[PDB]
Amino acid sequence: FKEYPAGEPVTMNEMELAAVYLQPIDMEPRGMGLPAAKADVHLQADIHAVEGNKNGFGAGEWIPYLTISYTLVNNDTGEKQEGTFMPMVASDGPHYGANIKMMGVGNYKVTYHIEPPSKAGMHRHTDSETGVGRWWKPFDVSYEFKYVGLNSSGLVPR
Amino acid sequence: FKEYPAGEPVTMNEMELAAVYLQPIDMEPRGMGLPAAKADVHLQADIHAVEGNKNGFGAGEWIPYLTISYTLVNNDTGEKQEGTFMPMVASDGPHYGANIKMMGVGNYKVTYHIEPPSKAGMHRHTDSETGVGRWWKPFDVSYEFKYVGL
Ligand SMILES: [Cu+2]
Ligand SMILES: [Cu+2]
């Protein structure tokens, strides 16, 4: 399937963090979250270790057990939306995301608010023999993108 | 670091599942965990996708968001201990595990009771465009090993 970048990926805390979006999706269980028919996009956080990660993840590996919320702003209109992502798995692997209703075509800012795996119940080893570095503190990452909508076969008859 | 196999790996539900143990470890956040000084081993489940996984995981990838409990039996005496594993990360990557006090040197069987990532809140996509196969049903896998101490 096709996916579209929302702004520029960034590196922070030995991870590469990107925002992306695609068409609304269906997830298990049915009836939970915003239904696809009532959404404009599935918004996602793509987060993987980079080389030199000190928390036990190899380059390219997904970072699991994160807690992530977002603040989305249409910069043209001022309209703001807040929400949370869930951990998910799709055909191209695990991610964090949510179906969302957008706030019209325009220039957007999105900020992801990220908390480390300790919060959701992952426990790092801390000893000399098997341990890893301490978790980083919660942080934000921001993205700027132009949203025009997604591809159609035709919105009106031809 | 040093690590000991508990039996051999198993391939089930498009995953390779192995049991290993090592010396007790320290972990954070501690919560309800058993301190290294009060344990005999750290027991672990190593669980990664194999080729052909239908749930969105590529070969060799860790399977995250599992809910795993164990039943450990000393086969010489019949004594049984039960407990839960936690998701963890060590210098060689993520696993599931727990510090455990054994029930003496001897022959042991450990059974891992495994529930799929839906239980712990990972949501699979289900649509034709982006979806993946249904989760397997919760299942057991067991391993035999000789605990002689460390
Ligand atoms: Cu998703
Ligand atoms: Cu562990």
Image (cartoon, coloured by chain):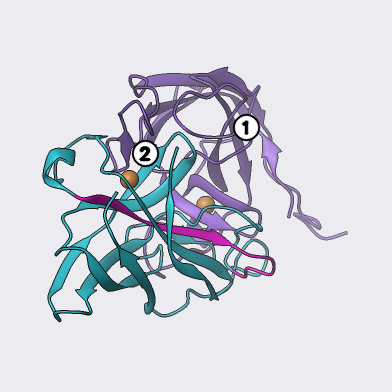
Chain colours: A purple, B cyan
Give the structural element (helix, strand or loop) at label 2: strand
Q: Magenta includes B47?
A: yes
Q: Is residue A66 above or below residue A115?
A: below
Residue at position x 50%, y 69% in the image: B8
Kind of residue at badge 1: Ala
Residue B78 point in image, percent of width and height: 15, 81
Circles 2 and 1, Cβ within 8 Å, touching? The answer is no
Of B133 and A35, the residue lying toward us: B133
Task: Identify the magenta region.
Answer: B40-54
- From the viewer's perspective, is B90 left or right of A142? left
Residue B126 at x, y = what percent?
55, 68
**Which residue in the structure is indicated by mark 2?**
A83
Beta carbon at label 1 within 8 Å of ligand 2: no
Left of A135 or right of it: where is B29?
Answer: left
Residue B126 circle label:
none
Residue A76 visible in this rendered orientation of the protein: no
In front here: B50 or A41?
Answer: B50
In the depicted structure, whether residue A79 falls above or below residue A3 = above
Subunit of mark 2?
A
| Tally of numbered discs | 2
Chain of the residue where label 1 is placed in the rendered structure: A
Report the amino acid beneath label 2.
Gly
Question: Considering only order in the chain, which callout, 1 or 2, is on the residue closer to the N terminus?
Answer: 1
Distance from the alpha carbon under mark 2 to that under mark 1: 29 Å
Front: mark 2 or 1? 1
Task: Read off the residue under disc 1.
Answer: A59
Residue B123 included in the magenta stretch of the image: no
Mark 1 neighbour class, 10 Å CA radius: few under 14, some 14 to 19, many 20 or more: some
**Horizontal side, residue B141 vs residue A10: left or right:** left
Q: Secondary structure at mark 1?
A: loop
The N terminus of chain A - image quarter = bottom right
